[PDB]
Image: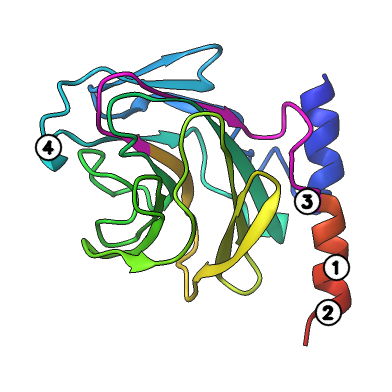
Amino acid sequence: QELSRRLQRLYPAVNQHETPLPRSWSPKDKYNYIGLSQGNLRVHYKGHGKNHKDAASVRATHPIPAACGIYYFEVKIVSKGRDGYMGIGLSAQGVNMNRLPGWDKHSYGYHGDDGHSFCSSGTGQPYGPTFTTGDVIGCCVNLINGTCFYTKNGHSLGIAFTDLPANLYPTVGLQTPGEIVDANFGQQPFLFDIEDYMREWRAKVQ
């Protein structure tokens, strides 16, 4: 399997038997307005999406193991759908899936339509560019420091969150009809050179 070899390469300190890595979205752990396809890697919004009370998220199958040191995943925007109310980020296991990532306690999100970050809060802060159909958004979590930065189309955007709690799950949320996103948990090469980033972080850490 190219997948297991890739993941062993990226995260050699991880005991995938004690703490398996997220490899796809959970077929269970999602709100009913979310549909899945393509081996649980594609996420479709299928609610009415009238307003933010129709937001809907999905969590990956497992939380990010601490021993990753630095973890990384990428999401491609297949379609913005109607409004592109799409959130990408991290959620703890108890987080309500009837919300976009970042709105609730222990939830962290970067949203496409405003480019704002949401740090366990219903109110966004200016963070990055907007994103839409065709864009690739990555999420890089530093488990050692408890920090997270995002990437857009291969380019890093700076730390969005600090003081992150342990055991967070990769999460995406959608809101409007037509919204579709694809996830890469390591199945294929990332746009962002994450291995080189890990070398640079070790090189520059103070």
Spatial separation of the CA atoms under disc 2 and disc 4: 44 Å
Q: Which of 88 and 125 is in front in this view?
A: 125
* Dot 2 alpha-carbon crowd within 10 angstroms: few under 14, some 14 to 19, many 20 or more: few
Identify which residue is drawn at 83% across, 23% down. 2
Q: Which of 167 and 124 is in front in this view?
A: 124
Spatial separation of the CA atoms under disc 3 and disc 1: 10 Å
**Amino acid beneath label 3:** Ile
Quadrant for the C terminus in the image: bottom right
Mark 3, residue position: 194
**Amino acid beneath label 1:** Glu
Spatial separation of the CA atoms under disc 4 and disc 3: 36 Å
Judged from the image, the secondary structure of the residue bearing numbered disc 3 is helix
Task: List x then y, in percent, for residue 135.
Answer: 56, 36
Give the foreground label among 4 and 1: 4
Task: Specify whether 53 is left or right of 186.
Answer: left
Q: Which of 93 and 123 is in front in this view?
A: 123
Q: Does the magenta stretch include residue 188?
A: yes
Q: Are circles 2 and 4 on residues that touch, CB within 8 Å?
A: no
Mark 2, residue position: 204
Mark 1, residue position: 200
**Amino acid beneath label 4:** Asn
Give the foreground label among 4 and 3: 4
Q: Is residue 127 magenta?
A: no
Spatial separation of the CA atoms under disc 4 and disc 1: 42 Å
Task: Specify whether 179 is left or right of 99.
Answer: right
> Of label 2 and label 4, which has the lower sequence position?
4
